[PDB]
Image: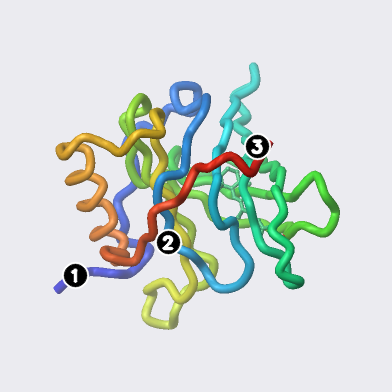
Amino acid sequence: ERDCRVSSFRVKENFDKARFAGTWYAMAKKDPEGLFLQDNIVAEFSVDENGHMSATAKGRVRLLNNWDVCADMVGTFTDTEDPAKFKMKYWGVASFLQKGNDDHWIIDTDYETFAVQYSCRLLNLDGTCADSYSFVFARDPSGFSPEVQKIVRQRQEELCLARQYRLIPHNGYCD
Ligand SMILES: CC1=C(/C=C/C(C)=C/C=C/C(C)=C/CO)C(C)(C)CCC1
């Protein structure tokens, strides 16, 4: 039934970088393998004059040594032939934080209430994702509307990630 091949996933039509800019609170996430931001996650997206999108993001993360630090992360997005699909090069302002290059797809957003992001880091041989992560972001760090939760749930099902997300606390700790 369900097509779970990554190449089949619908993304936001006519994605608008400039409209996406601003503050996005992470309200729920699906984690990938390995280290990952844990909670108190807020991203700030920017687009410069020449249309280049970037973002900073802050969140608590536990390092291999169980320290729970506030990470200040930086990403720069490279446009692709699909306006909703980017390559995100990222790093932290501390040198010990993870650095990498991930797909960054805007699965859906209405720009002023919610967004659903996705990254597949590794494809299975069948074209499904072997190692994904996904954030549900909000403009307002309260809960969402029933009507916006239902839409978010539909987008999670499109990604074959239904029931795989956890809610994210916001309770001080970071910057
Ligand atoms: C940069 C950035 C993002 C991803 C951050 C990641 C993937 C951080 C991982 C941090 C680690 C593992 C720290 C421990 O060393 C998201 C998608 C939120 C969008 C905003 C910009």
- Vertical relation: 13 (above or below) 121: above
Label 2 CA crowd tier, 10 Å (few <14, some 14–19, many 20+):
some
**On the image, which quarter does residue 3 sit in?**
bottom left
SS label for mark 1 = loop
Q: Residue sitting at 50 percent across and 22 percent down?
A: 18
Which callout, 2 or 1, points to the residue nearer the camera? 2
Residue with the mark numbered 2: 30
| Mark 1 residue type | Arg
Q: Give the image location of residue 25, x and y in percent.
A: 47, 37
- The image's mark for residue 2 is 1
Q: Earlier in the sequence, mark 3 or mark 2?
A: 2
Label 3 CA crowd tier, 10 Å (few <14, some 14–19, many 20+):
some
Q: Residue sitting at 53 percent across and 44 percent down?
A: 80
- The image's mark for residue 44 is none
Label 1 CA crowd tier, 10 Å (few <14, some 14–19, many 20+):
few
Q: Residue sitting at 32 percent across and 65 percent down?
A: 161
- Vertical relation: 40 (above or below) 24: below
Quadrant in the picture for the C terminus: top right
Q: Is residue 171 left or right of residue 68?
A: left
